[PDB]
Structures are given as C-alpha cells and as structure tokens.
Amino acid sequence: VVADVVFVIEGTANLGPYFEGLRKHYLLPAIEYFNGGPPAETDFGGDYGGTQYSLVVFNTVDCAPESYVQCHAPTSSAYEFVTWLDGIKFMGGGGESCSLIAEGLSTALQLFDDFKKMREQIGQTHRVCLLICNSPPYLLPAVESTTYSGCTTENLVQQIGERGIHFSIVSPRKLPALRLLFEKAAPPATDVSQDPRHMVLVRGLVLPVG
Amino acid sequence: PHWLLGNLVSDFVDTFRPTARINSICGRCSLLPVVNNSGAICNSWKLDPATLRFPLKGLLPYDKDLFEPQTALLRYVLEQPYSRDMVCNMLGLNKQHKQRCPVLEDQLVDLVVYAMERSETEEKFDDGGTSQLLWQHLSSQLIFFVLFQFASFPHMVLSLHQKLAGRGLIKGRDHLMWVLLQFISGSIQKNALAD
Amino acid sequence: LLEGTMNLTGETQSLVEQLTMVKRMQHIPTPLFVLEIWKACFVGLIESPEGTEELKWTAFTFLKIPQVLVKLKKYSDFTEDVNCAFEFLLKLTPLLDKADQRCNCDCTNFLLQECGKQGLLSEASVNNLMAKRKADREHNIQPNIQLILRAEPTVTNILKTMDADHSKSPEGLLGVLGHMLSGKSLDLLLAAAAATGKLKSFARKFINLNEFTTYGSEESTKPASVRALLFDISFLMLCHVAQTYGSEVILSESRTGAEVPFFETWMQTCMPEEGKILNPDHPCFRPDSTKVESLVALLNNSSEMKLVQMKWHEACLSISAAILEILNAWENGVLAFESIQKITDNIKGKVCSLAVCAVAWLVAHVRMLGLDEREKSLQMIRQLAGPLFSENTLQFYNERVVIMNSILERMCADVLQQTATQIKFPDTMPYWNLLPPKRPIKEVLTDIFAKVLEKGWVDSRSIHIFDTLLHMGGVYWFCNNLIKELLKETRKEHTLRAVELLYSIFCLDMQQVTLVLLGHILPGLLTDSSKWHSLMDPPGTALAKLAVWCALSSYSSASTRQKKRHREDIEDYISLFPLDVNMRDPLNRVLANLFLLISSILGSRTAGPHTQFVQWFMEECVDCLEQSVLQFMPFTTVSELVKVSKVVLAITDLSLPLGRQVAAKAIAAL
Amino acid sequence: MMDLAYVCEWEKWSKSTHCPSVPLACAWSCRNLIAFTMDLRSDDQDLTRMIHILDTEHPWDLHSIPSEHHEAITCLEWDQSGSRLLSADADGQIKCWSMADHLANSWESSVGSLVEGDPIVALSWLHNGVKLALHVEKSGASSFGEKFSRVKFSPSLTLFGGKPMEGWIAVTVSGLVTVSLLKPSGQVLTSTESLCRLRGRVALADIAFTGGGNIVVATADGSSASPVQFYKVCVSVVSEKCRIDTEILPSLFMRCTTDLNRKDKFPAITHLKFLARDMSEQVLLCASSQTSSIVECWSLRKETILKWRILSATNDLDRVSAVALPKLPISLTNTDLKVASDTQFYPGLGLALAFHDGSVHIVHRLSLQTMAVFYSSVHLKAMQLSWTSLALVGIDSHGKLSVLRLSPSMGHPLEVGLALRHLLFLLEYCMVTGYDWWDILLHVQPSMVQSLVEKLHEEYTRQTAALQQVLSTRILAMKASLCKLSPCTVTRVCDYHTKLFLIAISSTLKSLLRPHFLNTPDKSPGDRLTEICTKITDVDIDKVMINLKTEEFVLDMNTLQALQQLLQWVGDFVLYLLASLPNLRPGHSFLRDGTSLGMLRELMVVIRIWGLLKPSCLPVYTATSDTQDSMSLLFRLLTKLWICCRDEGPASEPDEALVDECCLLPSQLLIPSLDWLPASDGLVSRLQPKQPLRLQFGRAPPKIDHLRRLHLGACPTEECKACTRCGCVTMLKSPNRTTAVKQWEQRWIKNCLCGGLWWRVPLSYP
Ligand SMILES: [Zn+2]
C-alpha cells in the first residue's frame, strides 16, 4: 500500500561493523514488504503517488565544522534506496558514547511535513519511521533544525508518537534509553529479532518472525 | 609530420594540391540526387559505411570538406519517402547480414530530434504543415531500420535521451512516443524486455 | 575592408603607411596590390546594408581610395601598374555586375573617370578601358555616386558661403539648412566630408553657428522664431554627426581661453555614446535651483509665448533638473498623468532639441534605477519620443522629427534592451546587438574564425563581432584563443591564410596585441615543455611569420573602444619584465625580454621544435626587414645562431663600430 | 600591532625568468590549511598551475596538487567546512577538490563545471544558512548561548526538509552566471544564464548572499567611470533542472569622478568586494591609477526607495596590491561598537590593505581610518586574514610566504585581565564552533598560560550539562595545546593526551559488550560495571569479578583476540603508573585522580573476564617468578591507590605500605617503556615575539603506531599518517582487514583523537 518510509541511521563507528548484518536480516526485508518483491533496475522515480523512501543519516559532535545530518531526497525506487544504503560510510566517532538522535528525528519530522504537503490525493497514509541506532542519545536539544529547535529527544519522540507516525527501533546492542524512547512514541490509542543480542521493536511493518 | 622532416614533407604534399584540384567534382557536397526506388544505383552517391565519407581515389591532398562526414546528403535522402533501398545502396547494407551500423543510427536519431524541433516550432498554424507527414514517414523508415538490426533500439533511445536532455523540447512528445510505440508493438515478442 | 568599416574618418596618411608596411612585409607586386584594394572596396560595397553605410562605402571607394593611391604614387611607373590592375579587375565581370546592380549605374565608368581626374591613369588607358567595359557590359533618380561626386564640391562651397551666415541673412540660412534636412542630403554631405578629411571643419562651422544662435538679440516673435529654428537645425545635425562619425570630430582639441561652446560640453557630459555611461547626479546635471523653477513655470505657462529671449544653452542645460522635479512630482502622486502630457507637449512641440536633452538625462536616470522602479520614467520617454505634436510647429517640422527619431533610437537602444520594451519610433542600427544571448563567447569566436578561413576574407559583420569580442573578453583572451585556433591547423595552405587574416584582425589594437603576443603567448609556448609539440613546422612557420609582422608593424607604428580601454589600463611593465633607447616604453621591454629568451633557447641543450621556432623567427626577422626590431638583439645571438645554423649575421648586427667586431668574428669563422 | 611569525621561501626555485607574472590566489580554511598558487616557472608552466596546501603548524611540509588547469587559476575557495576546495581558472573549468582517504595530503577532484572559453571571474560556494553573531558585551555572561547566537539566516535552495543543497555559483567575464548543485548522490546539475539582456564585460565581480535565499552579484568592467551594476539571482530546482532568475538592482557610480578638480585620475576599478559574504548591503571599491588609489565603502540603505550612498573613503594611498576582509562575524551594532572601543577588542573591525611599497595597513571597517601600520623590511600580492582574525597570511612578489600576527588590541597596551578575557572569548568561539585555535596560540604569552587554563575550566563548568558533554575533548585538546606553551606547564601535556586515549579506549570497550539478555534492566552494562566496581572496594580481583554476571561479558573470540594490543596498553600503563608512584614525570597527574584510577580498575576487571574466556587476549608481563598472578597483583595495588582518592573531600597522601610494594614492582615485573603522544614539532612553542623564523620549503627545521599499538621497525616498511596537532602516527591501511576491531579503527578515519587532521608522511628509504 502507499507508504512514506523514512530511515534514520547513525553514521558513526558504532553501527559500523554491525550494519551489514542488520541490513540483510531486518532493513532489506522491510523495504521488500513495502515494495512487494525485491527491486532490480526497473523501478522508476517520479510517481508522486506511491511509496516514497528517504534517508536521514546523522553523526556525533566530532564532525565539528561539518553539518550534523545528511538527508536524501525522496525516491520512489526501492533500488535507488538500496544503493543509498550501500553508499553510507561509517567513519565518525571518537572519545564518546552518545550521538545526535534529536537532529535525525527533527529532520525526519521535517521530511514528514514535506511529505504531508506533497500527498494531498490521500489524506493520511502509512507513515513509517525507523531508527537504526547503536548509541544512547545526547542531552543536547536540537540545534540545526528550523521549527523544531530547542527540543529534546523526548519531546520530538512525543510528536512522532502523536499524529500517527509508526516509530521503530533496530539496534544491534540492547539498550535502556532506546527502549524508553520506543515506549514514549506510542501511536494514539512477536519476536522479530533473528539474533538474541539485537534489540528490534517495530510498531509498524511486518518482518519474518525468527 | 615528424619535427625533423617538417617543411620538407609538408610543402611536398602541398605541391600535390593542383592534381587533387583536378580530380574533384566541384560542389560535390551540395549535389543531391532525385530518389527513385528503381534500383540500379549510380555509384556516385555511395558513402563509406564506417565514416560517412566519400570514397576517394588515391591519397592526394583533397579539399578540406571532402574529408568530412556527408550528413547533409544522408539526411536529405532519409527525409524522402520510399528511400529505403537507396539508403542501403549508399551505405552498402545488404539485409542478408545484420550489422548495427552506427552512423546510420546517429543520423536517424538526429532526424528524430530535428522532427521534434520542427514540431515544437508551432505545428498549429497549418494542420498538415509537413509535420505530421514527417512523423508518419519517420515511423515507416525507422521501423525498417531498427527492425533488421541495422540500427539498435536501446542505444538509439538513450542517445535520443541525451540529445533531448535539457534542450526543453516539449510540444510534440506524443508523436515521438507514437513512433517508439510502433517499434515496441512491432517487436516486443522477439526481444527481451531489458532492451 | 577594416578601414572602410570602422574609421572612414581616419586620415589617409595612416592608411598609406599601413598599406606600404603590408606591401613590404609580404612582398606584394604593385598590380596585385592595387587589384586587392579595388576588389576589397567593391566587395564591401556590395555587402553593405542599405542606408547610411552604403553612402559611406560609396564615399570610401569613390573619394578616399583614389586619394590613397595618389599618396602611394608620390611615396613610390605607377600608371602602368594601376592600368594593369584595372585590366586585372575588368576580367571580373560578375563582381562588377553585382556592383552595378547595387550602384544602379555602371560604377566602373565613374571609377575610371575619377582615377583619370586624380592622375593615376593616362587618358588613352582610360578610354580603352571604358571601351572594354562597355563591350563586356553589352552581354530618373540620380545614383548615389553622382550625388556624392557632385556633393563634395558643394561641401567646399557650402563651407565658403556659410562662413558669413549668408551675409548674416538667417532666413537664407534657414532655407538652405531645410534643403539639407531634406531626404538624404545631410548624409551625402557628411559622407563626402568624412571621406575627404573635411568633417572637422564642417563640425567647427555648425558649432560656431550654434554659439552664434545660443543667446539671440532683442527681437520680435518672427526674427526669434527663426533663431530658435537655427539652434534646432545646428544642434540636431551636430548630434547626428556625433552619433554617426564618432564624437572626436566634434571636439576642438585646443580651446585657447575658457570659451568652449555649448554643444561640446553638452556632448562631453550629457550625451550617451557606445562606451560612455553617464552619471545622472553628476554636477553637470545640477546647474542651479533658481533657473529650473523659472523653467518649470515656463513649461507650465502655455505655448512658451516667450521664445523671444531664452538663452537656449541655459534652457537645455536646465531641462534635466526640470524633468527630475517633474518625475519626483509624479512619483509622489501630486501631478496627474494629464498634466504630464501637457508638459511633454510643451517640451517636444516648439523646439525638438529639448526632447533630446531630456531623453538623454532620462536614459542616464533609468540606467541607474532598479527593475521595479523604472516603470514610470519609461512613460516619459514614450511621450517625449512619441509622434508629432501639431498645429504650432515653427517650420521644417517633419524633417526635424525624422532626425530626432533617429537620435532617440540610438540613445535609448541599450536601456530598452535591458528590459524588453518596444518604443517603436517608425534599420539605422545595422551592426548592433550581434552576440547570441546565452552562448559562451568562445563558440562565437571559433565559429566566426572558421567561416573567415573558409571564405578567405573578413566580412564587415565579422569585423564588428571581432571588435565586440576584443572589447568584451579582453586582449589576452582574444589573442590566445585565435592563436590556439591557428595552432590546431594541419595544412600549409590554411595556416598561411589564417596568418594573413589574423594580422588584419589584430589590427584592431595592434599595439596591445603585440604586447600580449610577444610577452605572454610566445614565452608561454617557448618555456612550457609540454606546449612545444604545438610548435611543429606547418603551423609553426606561420606563427613565427605572424609574430615578426606584428613586431615590425607595432614598432614602426586604432579604434575608439581601444583608445578608451588603453586609457583605462594601468600596468607596470618595468615590474612585469624585470630584465635580469627609452626602455620605459613597454614594447622595447617586451622585445628585449623576447630576444633574451631566444638567445637562452638557442644556447641551451635539448633541441626540439622550439629551437626550430626561434630559428624561423630570426630568419623572418632577417628577411622581412629592409635595413629596427633587431636593435634589441643581444650580441651573443650573433655567435650562437651559426653555431645552430651569412646574411643572418650581416643584417642582425645593426653595424656599430663594436658591432663590426662581432660581425667579422662570426662571418669569417662560419 | 604586527609581528612576522615566519617567512617561508622556496629554495633556488625562484628567479622566474622571461615569462611575466600572473595574479595569485589564496584561501585560508576553517581548519588551518592555506591553499595558494604561485609563479614558480621552472622547466614547466604547470609550476604555475600547482595548488599548494600548507598546513599552518608545519609549513615546511607543503603539498602541491598538480591541478590540470590549462590556463591560470583565477579563484580558490574553501568550503563552509574545511573539507573541499573549489578552484576555477580562465576558460571555464571549475574543479572541486576533495580529500583522498581523508588525508590532507591527497586531493582529487571528481566533480566540476565547465563554461568553456569564458574566464571565471568570481566563484563562491552556496550558503548553507548557518550564521552566528558574537556579542562582545556579553563576554563575561557565563553562558555560550548569550555570547554566540544564531541569526536566523536562510539558505539559498533548500531541498525537501530544512537541508540546504551544496553547490557553487560562478560569474564569467562575459555576462554569464552558472550554478552547479551537488546532489546527495554523485549527480551534479549545472545551469548557465546571462545576468542581464544587455550582454557586457564583467571585469570584476563579487558574490554575497541575503536573508531570503537570494544571491547578489556585483559586476564592474574596470573603467571606474562606468556603473558598478548589481543583480539579484534566485536559484530554484524545476523538477529535474537548475533554474536561475536574475533581476537588476540599483547600480552605483563612484566618487572621485564627480570630484571636478582633477577627476581623470584613478581610472581603474581594481578591487570589488562585499564586506562579507552574507553582508550584501555594503560594498568596498578600490579605484586606482598607476600610482595612487582610493578605497570607498557604500551601502544600499533605503529612503527611489533603494539607493547607494557612500559611507567613507580614504584620502590618498599608494597603489593597493591586495585586500583582505575579515571573517569573524561580529555583531556590529552601536553598543558593541562602544564596548569594543572601550575594551580594546579589535579583531573583527579590520581590513588589511597591502600597498606597492612594503607597507600594510589595517584599517577600520566602517570609517576607513588606519588602525595600524606594518612596514615590510617587494609587496604582498595576496593576503588573507584568519577566521579568528588574529593572523594574516600573505604571498609576496617573490616566493616568500609570510604569516603576521595582529594583536587583538592593535598594539595598544592592555592590562593582563583584559588580554586574558579577549583570548578566552576567542577560544570559547573556537570551542563552540569547530574551528582551529592555532592563531590564538600565536598570541598567548607563556606568563599568562596557567591563568588562562584556569579560566577555561571555570567556563567548562557552569554550562548546561549538554554543552559539558559536547565540549569535553575540545577542551582537553585546547588545554593540552595551551599547556604546551609554557615551561612551567610543559610537563602536563602528556597527561592530557593519555587522558583522551584512556577515554577513547574505555567507552569503546564498554561499547563492545552487547548484553545477551537484559537482567536488572534500565542500566546498560557499562553502568552496571561502574556501579559494581565503585561499591565493591575489595582488594582482590576475584571478589569483584564474582559479582558481575559474567555470562554477559562475552565476545565472539575473534575480535576478543584482536583486542590484544589495546589490552596490552592498558596493562602496561597500569604497571608503569604504579611503578612510577615512588618518585614530575609522564604519569604524575593520574596518581591523584580518582576517576581515571576507577576507569583503570574497570578495564582490569573486564580484562580478567575476557582472559578467562580466551587467554590469548591478555597482556603479557615478563615476570621474575613463575608462581605469580600479575594481574591480581596490579589490581591489588591499584585498589589500594584508588581508595586513597575515591574518598569525599580527601587528598590522602599515599601510605608507606603502597610505597614499598610499588618499590618491589621492578623486582617482580619488568616495567617496559611507553610512547607519549605529543612529539612536539609545532612552531608555536618554537616561536618568540620580535623574532621571525626564516624557513625553506621542504627543509624542516622506537617508532610506534600510537592508535593501534603496533611496533613498527627501526625504519618502517609500511607508510603512515601523522596527526597535525598532537603528532601521533598510524599506519595508513589496516594490517589485517579481516581481523580488525572496526569499532576502534573506524573512530579515527577522518581525524585523530586530539582532533587534528591526518597528513601522509613520506617513507625514509635509507
Ligand atoms: Zn592528534
């Protein structure tokens, strides 16, 4: 069915080694579920009706004069999305444990606002957001965003949870903060983890049970 | 030439300029035939299928235009109705053997983009106005030349995409789509869909 | 063809010097030389656009070129050679028939009678040539050639009769001037006066007439209404001269005392030309506050009724401030559109020069403004340059309207090009806005040079586009790209033709082009180790020829854009060429630096194509010279050049007492 | 005031002969890298087409990109970050150089534009909408939100989100303008369009941006009696393609043409510059004759609604050879002008004007009155101020490249508290951004260093607990680089770098353990480990290891084996520290820091658990006995040291039992040796005021890999990167790509841990 899919990925050294495994087990099947059957080179962008994928990659504060979030424009090709998922290079990090989840979520919110101004042929669609993270959030409010500046991760994930965006978390290391954020993004009113170590909670989307 | 010979050879070839000047039909680039379907091709209009150049006797220093690809002659012949066998007799095509002749393919693409330009001029002042006649003849001619693999479909389409990229030629795109529909509807079952 | 297109008004001595130079560079026989002059003149006449340019071309061929030949005869058995060249030309029947169709008469007859009058040709030669031409020809309005050939004596006699204001009879002056304002008569007089060197005296005469009719004397309406018309006729013809033949014929070039005339200052500070953009709030456009209120009250009174004493220079200087206050009043809203129509009618009605002064200030002011702020002021031009106000015209109104519409076309054209606005006065601007709107300018340059090579000669339109590209991309870009397009030729014939054309193209600004060529292009080709594969024998011999022709012609020693731009230019050639006669003249510095480079290349190891280049450069320096560019050669080159392989010594040495010692050393020890 | 910090000259590669000079470009990035071109002219003209990258802390090492530019390079332009470099020459050809393998020594351009034949005369990156303003009157305000504040600027061409596109805009010598937009994918969209319909010469041009996402491009044709025209450009993307919409703005003429006394002099406009990109309303022009010149400042200010009026002009100068505008974005209003005149803060109010004699004038922004004068004792053909505007770099009319320091009060003497507050304000500005602070360390005297360090720590406190998170390693790097500058404080820098390294190991080891099941939830196993190690003060290692759920601390025994060298460094540093206890040395700070000793305890406990899982991961100690448990011995001594410092308000001097037991440690084990990171070759310690270093390019006035702790040989065979600030060396490509702990190696791909860039070092070949 029509879907506005937004992936939010932590592009840091953590999630570096574990990303290839996560893609085969969880991310790639999730794209197929939105796009029935695996994509191969015939899928064309430009159908404004239909499922539209997008990436948001974020970083920590060690990329000091560079920007924090790299966003990609929406595509209707699942194949271009797969090439974008290959094209991420995980180079960041340093002496820290946290990352800028608030930035990635705020730009995901701006993506969903631009999607909502885009699709008017349908009032509401399946608005799905995934967060592929390996790290607890920073305590910084969001700085490099307009209309969602000065907001912590809890406020932004409340605004994700209300208005009916289906929020999911795929993490290769089981963590408390990520679980708390997932519990908070509750939509108004099954073991999918193939590996025991992986923590995967999916509010929306169907992934083969393992 | 090599930097040690230099003038010694170059001036020598320049003294063979008058002999080449004797052996040149003057205004040969601008002489055009009347296309008859009769066959029995006069061998004056034969071009080289590799490079669209006139076949020249000798190694003389001929005039600078005779070393250029004669695209004007080939476009004039392709724009005429019933110039099917004459283009094969020009470019040496044989129809027992399929070849993917490239310069024919590029000339057909440039003919399509010229038709698209001339359709985008107005096409609405005169209803017939030679535009839709040109598109019908383009349909027939291009069906034959892509069908026997003298040219190929996907290289033609993507080169056509590179010519129309950014030029902003949109008023008669329906005609171009119609011509492509003639190819696809003619030969979808023979080739794979990736073509 | 260049001197015909750009400076018809140039002196013949510069052209004779340049042509004798070209005849000495490439050794040209005299019959082929004069044949190329006549062929160029006729081809340029045929390719001329209809209008003033055709009159100018008829004058250049009929009057200036015969005078040039006479000067060549004095400087140089010329009659036999010009007769040979005339038979050479009379073989070319299609050229002469195309010319005769444009001339509407046999133009070769007028040429042969004119060259008979000047004394280039003997009379028997003239008569058998006209017999041959009539035999080859066998297989109500006067044409322009008769009009021009008879109009040049009228130029001299009109000078001598209007020295004295027709014995101070202004009614007579007005009638004769109205006859001049009639169709094409002014243009005929100006073309004849330009081709024959008498445009300066003509401009002095109309300027002095203007100064006489500026103030006026105690008068009733009928005498003053003549004096204001004399101001209009003199002003409008002076503006037409300055817009057609350049502004430098209007200048006085030495005014002892402060009494510069009104029109010279107005043209200096207030009239748009091609390369002149004007400051609308220059102090020239703000004369007073006292007179301008009297003038706006004057324009709001009614029909002036007070033309009996106006001091027209003061009025014309004050219109700019007047229409500035009118514009501020209309921008606030305190003035209605209908009163604006009344003020524009009071300006443009009785005297037409007021409209020209106002439109000049309006063009400056609209050029300074932004996009959205312009909309009102353009309407002012639409009313000032509109069709005629009627029923109170003094006399000769339609002809002044026609001349004024031409002047306002050439004033407004640039501003009305910036925003797409059609004012539609009714070609009169045949070579204007020639470049394509979006295409990068190297494509323009390479296409025009490709067509000039494939023809074999340079058109008039091609000369104008080459001028605009030299002004636009600058000298270095121009000369470098044309030399690149030379160096990718591979044939001997095309390289020699390209060089013979590029010399004439570089004659737009020869001096600056030689500084760029021998200073930047050639040292960059000789010093770069990757570049000198481009210096192979086919293009390389041609390039060495072009460099030495450029060096000689710049040493022995021209358009108005080029004059303005070299006056703009600041550079320190002492700092550019540090160098390890004057030697503060930059060309001597470039030549000394180039010869140091040539000696360094000849002396070094690793002989390649660049060594062949500097060999060829020195050989055509020897051959092209009469005797001096080679005065700057270092004396070590005398030794080294025969180390790398007689006359190349004995010419290059310049023969000082120490110079004999180096000469006798090299020649004996070959 | 002005002091020449250093003069770097080419050796024997000057004396350009027989080919005339060319104008130079110069560009100082946010990271301190100068990109510049010079007229070398020896055996090739490509020696005038090489782009030299000079890291400003190690100038001898000059990289030389052989750009493939067939004509002379007009413009160089760094990114808004410091990571890409745009270079454009005559005849089109804009190239966009990016780093290769994140080395500052290898550049390669894959992306570029081309408008063939037309010379590029202005070039700029597009604006990304980030702009901040510095309130100097709030320098003491104790919160960084009050000192530096973002000013709500809009980026030209936002694309589907808040995210700006990156791209450039160039202006040719014809009327053409071109915009190239880089996609997030490798695609690039180009579009060219004429500026106005009247196509004309553009001999000088400049580009500023506005709020609202409009570019404002100023054109002049050099004649100085013709108007300096202005165009508003608006970029858009229509469905696949860039689209440029231009509109004429009010032009200006220039004074000294309406002077009417002698108006004919100064006939050439030679420099046109907006006062800063994103400050589009003020314009600096420079008319010049052959000998004299005039600079002028103009402003658009409205009343004809918009109209250019003059602000100020100089009287008469020498011929201005180069012009450098500042980059520090001061707040520029009236109160801040007052307080920056009272407290003599002058970093953002200066332009530098070189002249055709030796002199250089630092002149005011608003009313161009000369603030300082530096006589060279030959002219500056290119100048550039720094991002904190304390130093200006400049290329001369020879091979010489010089760096001058401008004092922040321009030579007027200040009391020490004001100089402290100025330099502290700038270091805080470099801390909030990510810019480099090297130019500040040009101005720090030794005698103030310690006081400055104190102020940094007091400003590291009293921020709002997320700033303290994000400014940790930046303030450790700034503390180390400051403490390098004084002989009293030179001993502590090693400690700071090991402190960085300790945290860099500690978190990563606590990052590797993925808890297989969540027992006692809401605490991650890093925090469970820290809680358990801080409440259990048992001196034995077994009694701590028992209570720590050791089925959770499991790895795959492959990465667990590959962690051997980092665990070796942990054990060796602990042993070195405890043996160093009886004695100012490389370990003196750690003996009294309770937190670092706690971290070392936690790592020893997880090392013990991982050794029980696989015994090959353990560090090795050459023991002078065979019935010994060396790990338990070191843990006993570490707990007995740490219980000294884990007390509340303690400062307990260590008792004599620990002293004699740690005297016995060289008897029981062999204390190996250690490499300490800041191998100092930085110039700032070497420099002195009033003495300039005269350097040659390429002359440069127990080998370990410090990040993966591998011993290279005597003369190492594999090639290496060196950090540009601390000096740590790593080998360039990983030794075993299969067994590589990518959680540790992928942290330092783009930078070092101290923050500086990597820089490829050449092999010896002895
Ligand atoms: Zn470092």
Image (spheres, coloured by chain):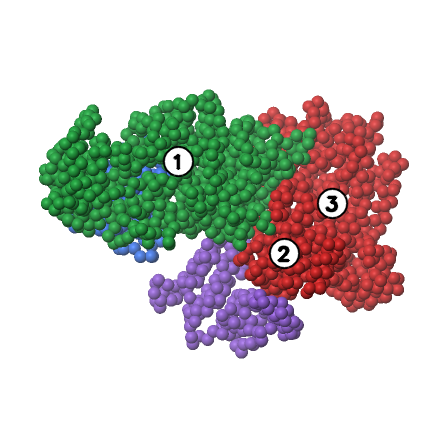
Chain colours: A blue, B purple, C red, D green
SS at mark 3 in the image: loop
Judge from the rendering whether residue D218 lies leftward or rightward of residue D165; answer left or right.
right
Q: Are marks 3 and 2 in contact (CB under 8 Å)?
A: no
Give the label on residue D685, or none. Answer: 1
Residue at 31%, 26% (x, y): give it. D458
- Comparing marks 3 and 2, which lies closer to the viewer? 2
The residue that disc 2 covers is: C599
SS at mark 1 in the image: helix
Pointer 3 or 2: first along the chain: 3
Asked whether the residues under marks 2 and 1 belong to the same chain, the reply is: no
Q: Is residue D241 above or below residue D402?
A: below
Residue at 47%, 57% (x, y): give it. B163
Along the viewing direction, whichever of C415 and B64 lies nearer the viewer: B64
Q: Amino acid at mark 2?
A: Ser
Q: Are marks 1 and 3 in contact (CB under 8 Å)?
A: no
Residue at 63%, 63% (x, y): give it. C644
Q: Where residue D242 sits: x, y (%)?
A: 46, 46
Q: Where residue C382 sits: x, y (%)?
A: 65, 37
Instruction: Give how far apart the Cα atoms at labels 3 and 2 are.
Output: 47 Å
SS at mark 2 in the image: helix
